[PDB]
Amino acid sequence: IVDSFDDMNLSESLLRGIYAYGFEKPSAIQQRAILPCIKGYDVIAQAQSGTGKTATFAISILQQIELDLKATQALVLAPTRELAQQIQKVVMALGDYMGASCHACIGGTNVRAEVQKLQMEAPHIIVGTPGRVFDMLNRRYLSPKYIKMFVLDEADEMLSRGFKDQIYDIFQKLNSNTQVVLLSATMPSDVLEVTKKFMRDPIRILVKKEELTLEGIRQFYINVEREEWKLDTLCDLYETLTITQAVIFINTRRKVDWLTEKMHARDFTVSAMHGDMDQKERDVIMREFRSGSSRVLITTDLLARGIDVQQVSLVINYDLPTNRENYIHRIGRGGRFGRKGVAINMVTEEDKRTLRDIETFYNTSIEEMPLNV
RNA sequence: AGAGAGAG
Ligand SMILES: COC(=O)[C@H]1[C@@H](O)[C@@]2(O)c3c(OC)cc(O[C@@H]4O[C@@H]([C@H](O)CO)CO[C@H]4OC)cc3O[C@@]2(c2ccc(OC)cc2)[C@@H]1c1ccccc1
Ligand SMILES: Nc1ncnc2c1ncn2[C@@H]1O[C@H](COP(=O)(O)OP(=O)(O)NP(=O)(O)O)[C@@H](O)[C@H]1O
Ligand SMILES: [Mg+2]
């Protein structure tokens, strides 16, 4: 445990970028994981939502970069285009002063423009989503020759059944000596088993499941009775609220579109976000929510992981998540870096089992919503 | 399953 960025043997010009970004003291995960990452160990880093995992790996990557080698030295993957873009902006701002280059390799962007930029000069760090990154590797416009660090953010999503093969196909193009770093708020037992295909006696920084939920996010439930409409329950509640910014999670794209329309039909101002929209529209919606121009986003799990909007203080689970790990991530959209937030769960009878599994596994208190608001 | 995840 190192409690000061000055105590981490970081180059002075990386420190200029850290302090310019506004950080003053390292968070708990930063105090524990930056040094092992810099030293080149494989690291599994679990830590509570919103406590600074991004800068943990960005700082470690930037300290390792050989700036005058104009070649890609580090590859970071994320499960969604929005998260990859967010991560890219953090690395680029931390690395700006020292002159590290960081390029986003994500789907839905002009390929010719990207290929020309890569042809101009290989960026030091690539942050991307797996499909586009593997495409660029396969076309040979991205070279793995000097990649010595491979970071999976949201690692347990990236190593799930639907992604692990994409990750493994990219991993095949990397040198055997590549350092591997995995970070997530959740690290379930099945994923930790999978990590042996990727990693060599790694350092494990884990959180006890009964201590994972954030103290500052008050969790509540509302029972929806059999004859009641969940839509009325949300609208009645939504009226009695003064929102700064809020996220409402829905399990399907179809239902996001439907709910957005219903809410507009009751003169509520919301915007919708999901993965079947054009990337230009996704970018606009995200930008307007980050800036505070729209106050309430209705979304799928596209935005459950990693997305950081400080002003979000309210999460509503209109549908409960289909796996318990996404519960942690969804409610973690509020309460970023020690702010107090609220999460509200709508619970129909068929939802009780799901919510019960969440409560007992994480040993967390979910209380009946009071009238205080 | 859902949700994500290249190009054309
Ligand atoms: C089991 O096979 C796979 O894992 C493959 C396929 O799944 C794959 O083709 C694949 C998709 O299939 C429907 C969809 C996909 O995203 C969706 O659809 C995109 C397009 O619309 C659909 O093509 C648009 O964006 C996404 O919606 C927004 C990415 C993707 O990448 C793949 C791929 C295949 C070849 C390739 O270079 C030759 C690059 C990517 C997977 C892959 C394989 C290795 C490494 C990473 C990813
Ligand atoms: N040392 C720090 N001091 C102050 N703010 C910080 C520090 N590190 C990170 N932050 C901010 O805390 C917020 C959360 O950081 P982020 O890296 O997104 O968290 P995370 O641990 O990855 N959360 P998640 O992916 O949802 O599990 C961002 O606004 C960061 O700028
Ligand atoms: Mg994160």
Image (cartoon, coloured by chain):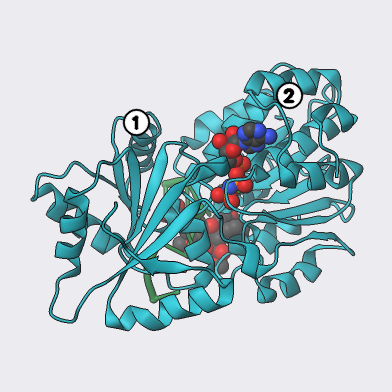
Chain colours: A cyan, B green
Name the chain letter of the residue that bears numbered label 2.
Answer: A
Quadrant in which residue A353 is drawn: bottom left
In the rendered structure, the answer to whether residue A82 lies left or right of residue A361 reads: left
- Rendering coords of residue A357 (x, y %): 49, 79
Amino acid type of the residue that numbered disc 1 sits on in the rendered structure: Gly
Q: Is disc 2 surrounded by few (<14), some (14 to 19) or many (20+) residues within 10 Å?
A: many
Q: What SS does tag 2 mark?
A: loop
In the rendered structure, the answer to whether residue A280 lies left or right of residue A54 reads: left
Residue A112 seen anywhere in this rendered image of the structure: yes
- Rendering coords of residue A320 (x, y %): 37, 69
Residue identified by numbered label 1:
A292
- Rendering coords of residue A260 (x, y %): 20, 52
Q: Which mark is residue A191?
A: none
Q: Residue at x 29, y 43 (%)?
A: A296
Amino acid type of the residue that numbered disc 2 sits on in the rendered structure: Ala
Residue identified by numbered label 2:
A100
Badge 1 or badge 2: first in the primary sequence:
2
Q: Residue at x 53, y 37 (%)?
A: A85
Q: What SS does tag 1 mark?
A: loop
Q: Nearer the viewer, residue A49 or A76?
A: A49
Q: Nearer the viewer, residue A334 or A281?
A: A334
